[PDB]
Image: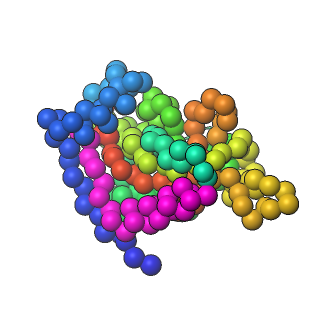
């Protein structure tokens, strides 16, 4: 075992990288004021995420395996996520609706809810802009611990994630370590 070593680089508003994260965010969260957008540089978590991506790309054909989603969390889970990512222990902070794992919203305004990006003592809310390996997904249920198996004859091979609606997804549930990378942290208020 390694990692637990990361750097946090604050993006300057003059920087286009900032305006791109802010634009995807403002599509649903234009009513909030961004205090800072930081980039989370965890090399060991990133290398493990890329190696999972190389595998998914080599098995899911034409599928765009990676999506950039949102994850709202409390002020105190920021150290944890920045070190471990969204590991199996962090599952116990999320819901169970579509299975035991980590939930990611498509629209930042779902993740902006006070139940998820709980405002701290200063009133700051934390929403991550995560790189998620969504791959091939099915419909989820509360009883899941691992994604359902694709084929009944071949049940060793399973779905990569689960969603609320397969034709019009709004949220995804990831179940394995290294499936999600907390690339950006968006800190904001009301
Ligand atoms: C059904 C549904 C949902 C959904 C949609 C978006 C998010 C999200 O952006 N982050 C998280 C993890 S933070 C969290 C905090 C408290 C609770 C709770 O009290 O149930 C759930 C999740 N969970 C999310 C969840 C659970």
In the image shown, does 134 or 74 lie closer to the viewer? 134
The residue at the point 33 percent across, 65 percent down is: 43
Q: Is residue 50 magenta?
A: yes
Q: Is residue 115 visible?
A: no
Residue 161 image point, x, y percent: 62, 49
In the image shown, does 100 or 150 lie closer to the viewer? 150
Q: Is residue 130 visible?
A: yes
Q: How is the image coloured?
A: rainbow
Residue situated furthest right in the rendering: 153
Q: Specify the principal SS of the magenta part.
A: helix
Residue range (magenta): 35-59
Q: Specify whether 176 is left or right of 31.
A: right
The residue at the point 37 percent across, 68 percent down is: 44
Residue 63 vertical position relative to residue 115 in the rendered view, above or below: below
Residue 146 image point, x, y percent: 69, 58
Q: Does the magenta stretch include residue 7?
A: no
Which image quadrant for residue 165? top right
Residue situated furthest front in the rendering: 62
Q: In which quarter of the image is the N terminus?
A: bottom left
């Amino acid at each position: 075992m390694k990692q637990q070593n990361f750097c946090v680089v604050e993006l300057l508003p003059s920087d286009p990288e900032y305006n791109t994260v802010a634009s995807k965010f403002n599509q649903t969260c234009s009513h909030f004021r961004i205090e800072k957008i930081e980039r989370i540089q965890n090399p060991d978590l990133w290398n493990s995420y890329q190696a999972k991506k190389k595998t998914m790309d080599a098995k899911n054909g034409q599928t765009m395996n990676e999506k950039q989603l949102f994850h709202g969390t409390d002020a105190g889970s920021v150290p944890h996520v920045n070190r471990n990512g969204f590991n199996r222990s962090y599952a116990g902070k999320n819901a169970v609706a579509y299975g035991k794992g980590t939930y990611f919203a498509v629209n930042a305004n779902y993740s902006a809810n006070d139940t998820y990006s709980r405002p701290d003592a200063n009133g700051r809310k934390h929403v991550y802009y995560v790189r998620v390996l969504t791959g091939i997904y099915t419909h989820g249920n509360h009883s899941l611990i691992v994604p359902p198996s694709k084929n009944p004859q071949n049940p060793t091979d399973l779905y990569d994630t689960v969603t609320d609606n397969v034709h019009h997804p709004s949220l995804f549930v990831a179940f394995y370590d290294y499936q999600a990378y907390p690339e950006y942290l968006i800190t904001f208020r009301k």
